[PDB]
Image (cartoon, rainbow, N blue to C red; front, top):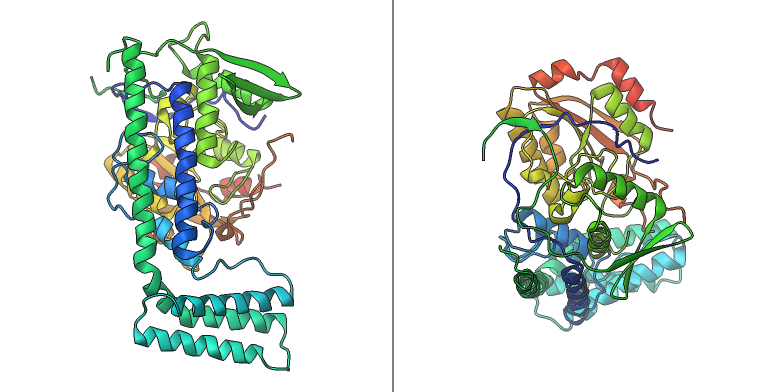
Length: 482
């Protein structure tokens, strides 16, 4: 439907030992869900009590992505051992909404209210918090200048109101940041430390469950890739019940229900048949589907396009396979993947559905790959370092075709590094990420993506010889856009 699970892999890796993840269990997934909900509530109260703002939209989810890049802890989702403690992602996102969040504007009275709301918010901040005398008089002058300019009987237009806000924000920004810096850092630190405590509780409950089940807790051939295997045996399956309401699969575990479309459920059964080797009678299938859906609900609120990751059209994947031999997605999930082989964030549960684990821990010696990472610049930067490390270590055909938003104000360090890479064979611009129909029946597309999508070809010499981005192959890839 929106996938081609018949295409076989051409990724080649060293044979690796089974991973030591604790086997997922709906009882533990439910506890992680209820603690992640409490963690979001701590984040909402900290932003409200310390800065008088709501949490910046999608910032908690983006925090989870950034923390995943550096976390050395034991939970597959929540952080517990991170250097730095202070997330640069969450810090930058909170600071962008201080003193207030800038909302979408369409009319003149909206722009006038937004300009006035910013000015009095900066004044209320100056009047109630510690600030150096230099920063106090600069903000005070700009706020007084704006208030008196609004007091003119001569009324300006909407673009005049907007430009006045852009300049006022330009002048007060540095002083507002120096005022709130210590407080925002404290929010990032406290939410990380609370998460670490939650991780310790989940870990202990999971070890206790396995002990209650009497469950105890390599050669380097080159082989075609294969899903991540677990070394710890699966605990006895639990009672998960399935029924369909119209074309929606409904799975209940002890009265707790998760939902997924019928089309995706049938896709998961196929991936499971192609990827799972420890459940010949599908006795554990429904339990693992429940954990999979719940895990991604905890990660991304629920189960087309958001402010975290874009979707590529199906014909683009077809053209990538036919024109450049692509068989593998570096950033996908069992729910959204196009190929049956992919890298994903949660190998403890995704491995049963074809995951090869996170890409930053994947070491292919050969293969043709596609990558459209989530909209997390910290992950993207680690991605580029991994790309160049892999391309420089192997002389076998290796190719990566990367899709990232064409944003230049300012460009991410990852995009700048890729444009200067010694492996860059070709670069172009394709249409922007847009909503791709899947549901059957939503958040808006990330703002950085609206100008278009940069497509970068990173190949070693063997890969450039085998999958060269010739003019004819580029036109066919461009022809895939409807």
